[PDB]
Image (tube, coloured by chain):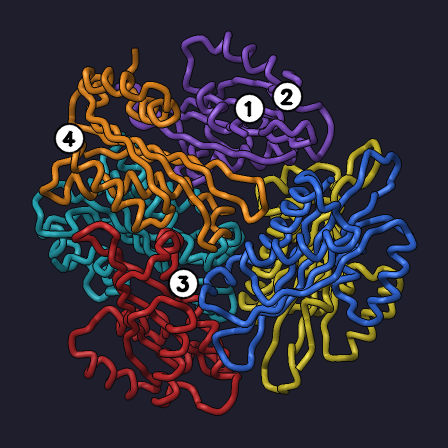
Chain colours: A yellow, B blue, C cyan, D red, E purple, F orange
Amino acid sequence: KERRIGRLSVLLLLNEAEESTQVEELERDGWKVCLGKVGSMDAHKVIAAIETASKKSGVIQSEGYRESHALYHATMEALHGVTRGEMLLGSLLRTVGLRFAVLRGNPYESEAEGDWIAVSLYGTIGAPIKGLEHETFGVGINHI
Amino acid sequence: KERRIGRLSVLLLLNEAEESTQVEELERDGWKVCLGKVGSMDAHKVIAAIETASKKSGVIQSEGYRESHALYHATMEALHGVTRGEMLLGSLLRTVGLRFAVLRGNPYESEAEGDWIAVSLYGTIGAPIKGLEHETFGVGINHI
Amino acid sequence: KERRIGRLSVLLLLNEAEESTQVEELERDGWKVCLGKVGSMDAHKVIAAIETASKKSGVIQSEGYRESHALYHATMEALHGVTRGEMLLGSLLRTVGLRFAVLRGNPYESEAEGDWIAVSLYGTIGAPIKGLEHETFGVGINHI
Amino acid sequence: KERRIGRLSVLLLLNEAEESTQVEELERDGWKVCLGKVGSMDAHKVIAAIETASKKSGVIQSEGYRESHALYHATMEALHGVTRGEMLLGSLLRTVGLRFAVLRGNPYESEAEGDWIAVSLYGTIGAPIKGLEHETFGVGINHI
Amino acid sequence: KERRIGRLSVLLLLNEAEESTQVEELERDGWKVCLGKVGSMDAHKVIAAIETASKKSGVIQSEGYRESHALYHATMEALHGVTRGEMLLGSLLRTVGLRFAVLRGNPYESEAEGDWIAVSLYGTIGAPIKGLEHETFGVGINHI
Amino acid sequence: KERRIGRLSVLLLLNEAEESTQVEELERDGWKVCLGKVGSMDAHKVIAAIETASKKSGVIQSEGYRESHALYHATMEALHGVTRGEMLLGSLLRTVGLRFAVLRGNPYESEAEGDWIAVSLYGTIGAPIKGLEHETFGVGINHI
């Protein structure tokens, strides 16, 4: 079995070449995809943005603690990577872009309910002068 | 075309297909490259392997602790990413297969203060449960 | 010695059969008991509710950093369990009941000052539709 | 009478007295039960013991990874609870005695989507100091 | 090599005898010093106070993610010590003094860029009645 | 002149020069002292060494667990400080040299409820990278 939901989510996040085509390629292969961008690294904002863009994309249904809890946790896991192990400081981070991806589906060929979600995050921390000063990555993977 | 060493690091790491050509273009574009793999997630083990495999090539200069230390911190941040926390509850001699990519060059955004160095980690940790592996991911960027 | 202050606090928390009788049974056996309920899983709210209900019950005296610090820490420890390792998310948790217990006294027969406190928490995370969707537990034990 | 699998799990775990009758009533009420004990806090060790002791009885079906994996995650969450963090500073071959309770059935609240599975852990970790043991507690609930 | 930037920062923090003379002694020895005091243990406040007093003292230049990130992290590291492993609670801590020190320079004789920063923090947690009830310490050391 | 046992602890610990005179003045001022050193960062190892070296002198009375336990908790808090978290990723038999200072007396601020006990830790952990050591620091204060 080689359906790396994590690897996938990160590749979708970086391959901005033709993400339009990638999302469908993956969509038809039993995946629920969602790409988005947030201009903050504050935990609450990121979650709200991801959640919204997740429900509005059918990646997660509008109500249900179960799925929200999974997205939330995978998201939190990935935020620890993008904020460089300092959650609290991500909030303080000004002038920062965050691109996110979220994949949901079976991590393997077993038709059985093996339903996982992956939240990949790509951060660009820049300043008014130059533009990019430091990049950050994060990945969270949880079963639903 | 962007000169994002981090993004490049992960793309190089995450695309096993024709790493040869991917590496050729990177070397051809003023980047020093270095790929590898390690069966240990142990700090000591990972850092030795990386430091060694990087010096052998033209990544860092085997001479002063300056470039060496810069590699260490980038690798630590990267490892700190692979050793999320749940994998931390996994202290029982497991089958861990890490693959790494090291990229050293200059994010020539505007100025060329100096060189930068990125370390990307990706592998799969076996689960104590049969037929189950976890994906781990980590990135560490530092200024030489 | 078998005075499990933790085991006790959890049993008091679940045995809603006749908690009225349990509290006295334990009260007379050198214990300072306190039961309460909070309609949130946000750290600050829980602490404020527990603290208040703790002082007003004589389980902790109104002023004194020492005792507050112990209750606070045991509480924090138990919150990590009830929020399923995700403090921050407990705050975001809507429609959620939290029942708490707090015991204070000697964990053993040594009349010497062996004074500990235990905060047991039982969480019920429900939604407007059904009612219960997931339960959570947490326990914190600190010496004063 | 409530059908809270979690609450039941902990009550079964925390009441050693006449577990026989407690188990009888649970089995008689459409629940699959399973008790045990383990002298290791090591993930690998705990999960093996639990998975094995649960399959032997009618908890999960020894056949597919579906029920097996569901047991794993519930046990991990539970263990993640026993390995709070202070016990994490305790990596020196200590005397740890964990007792576990596994309950698999259906929280028949309204609908019967499917079965649920809860794992309760309770034990006592010896302290590096003479005459002192710490109580550990953890619960993990999952949907089959 | 014996330039203990950490040891130094703590000694400067406690030696209130003649800190006026110490700061210069160290200033002339390739160090960027900064002493300050905050009447809170809330993460955000401490960081804002330290940052401000850090830039206004030339210990860190006004703009630049790199240096801010280092101070921020060392600060965060030291706060975990002063709040006794409970970040969140430090915020709740009322009637509390925090003295801080910050050193920046080369941790060794290698003229090469070995540039680190250390944030030492000394906390005094008192009440309206007596005055001091408990003291706390924290130290963070990061390379820039 | 202040009677801050913590501050004194760290000063005693951090000043190796003429510890003899520093100790003389402390003993002469109603304080019980105790210095030492340990090559292990292992809880079990550190606590044994400290507990033993403290009983030999007039720090705690080798008789009851009361003073013994009080020493344990203070040492744990202190160790919890030395085992920050990054040193936690360092589980590979490293060269760790901890030095400790134990001070037991009475912070006679106003009242003399009873005695207090402080434990200070300072050492240097070797890095997996050549020519690099990390400083560790921790303090734990407890009421006898």
The picture places residue C124, in percent across and down from the top left corner, at 41, 62
The reply to whether residue A62 is visible in this rendering is no
Q: Which residue is tagged 2?
A: E59
Query: What's under tag 1, amino acid-wise?
Result: Val
Q: Residue at x 37, y 78 (%)?
A: D50
Crowding near pointer 1: few (<14 within 10 Å), some, many (20+)?
Answer: many
Q: Which mark is residue C136?
A: 3
Residue F46 position by quadrant: top left
Secondary element under disc 1, as helix, strand or loop, is strand
Secondary element under disc 3, as helix, strand or loop, is strand
Residue F37 position by quadrant: top left
Q: Nearer the viewer, mark 3 or mark 4?
A: 4
Query: What's under tag 2, amino acid-wise?
Result: Val
Disc 1 to disc 4, C-alpha distance: 37 Å
Establish whether labels 4 and 2 are both on one chain.
Answer: no
Query: In the picture, which quadrant includes the N terminus of chain D?
Result: bottom left
Q: Which mark is residue E102?
A: 1
The picture places residue D13, in percent across and down from the top left corner, at 27, 72
Chain letter of mark 2 equals E
Crowding near pointer 3: few (<14 within 10 Å), some, many (20+)?
Answer: many
Crowding near pointer 4: few (<14 within 10 Å), some, many (20+)?
Answer: some
Residue C1 position by quadrant: bottom left
Relative to B79, is C121 on the left or the right?
A: left
Q: Which residue is tagged 4?
A: F58
